[PDB]
Length: 306
Length: 306
Image (tube, rainbow over all chains, first blue to last red):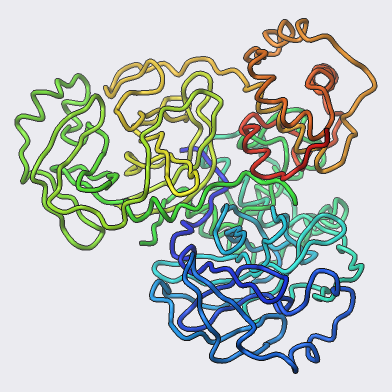
């Protein structure tokens, strides 16, 4: 029993974290097969980040300038290239610690594990979610660029996030591992407004679904409410609307609790309209939108990777 | 920046995660050098768990009765022994994935990362704290005994936990790696009492300092309160008492922020008497006792002026 925000075992990823130093900048790279992925902004120093023409900045550049190193061993680039907002560079030797892996871009509301790294060495691991305004709530300090976001299925490690920078509203933005930013964001350092954020409803539903799994009944209430009055009180309290698709993703948990996915919405309305009235669901008076239903099953079943 | 319950990279431990099977029972072992550590009650059937004589059960069991496997390849047990409530298995070959490590006992209110395991295969990583009543609130289903607790300091993984059981209120109890349970518990199906639990004061005090690092002071207050009448309203709100030593380890967070531990103490007492009035400190309407001041420094860099 018990329920905790849970990260995947970082082990398959740690082996790919390397330090890249190009000029005055140092950040982290992803050493997969025989190529290192890292944020496009390694070629530019911290002073000229206002508006660099990155395409022009690379035209003069050559392989030899880049010092990519694994722990202590140094590596040389036999080919450099820029795809979107990464700088994928082919190195002399492959990484034999490369796991089975996939590149994926995830849609707002999913969750993943982050492996924070500073100067090529992982420092920490935690669990976040792509916010509906295309941000994340991370812990990233200086020298943390290129720290990755990932999921695991069996042997396979699908990477889904690579860190680029911090917004003036405290949050972070980056790209997918194809180098394409998440959200109305860009790398060039500018005032980008962290859009307004809505609560991910289906993920709050799932966390209530961990709750009755864990043996919490406080919020339970019998009377039910229409599908669309949910969408109605959803927009009222800045909650993302439910679709039938979510009702189907909740299907797997539906039978296991024995509650219809609709009835819990009504108990949710009780939480949202009446407030928590000073009590706790799964050790939180906060409604939690940072858990997807795959997240809840992985913890109540206890699936594994190896 | 930002603040997250963050675990250490579990990679160094995963290489030691191994499966142990005795009879009909399977749980996890800690494969360090050429010995596997695991909870002693794997020699036990569900029948003898009510009252076991472990010495007798272990003589009856032999080298060949123990099956330790790498999720894949089998390993050979050429020696078994019992240290308190663990079970050292001298295995034929050493583990070339052995980290630098320490066997360590931690004090209540300290924190560590747990790597949950099932059939020798990891499932997840998260952050905990040994509670003052000597429990932890984990995520543990069946087949998770022998999941270890660890920290990482530079290279070495100071080990501090091997999980044994679940208490009737949902929480968990286990041992150190010398085999000694934290708390008045032992491995025997009995009426085992989960003691009453108090909140870790020093961690909340520290956790307020992550909040002023965020630079939001809504909780900061003009009102001051004395040091020792606090220890009194502490027992009133079931908090373990603050000590001066606690304040000296907390001092480093004080000096870099410039807040005296006393006024943060006063803001806390005022905070608990009237409540937060529906506002949130670091995205939580619940106070956090699971962050050490070392945790707060490990996550906030800070600097100190003199």
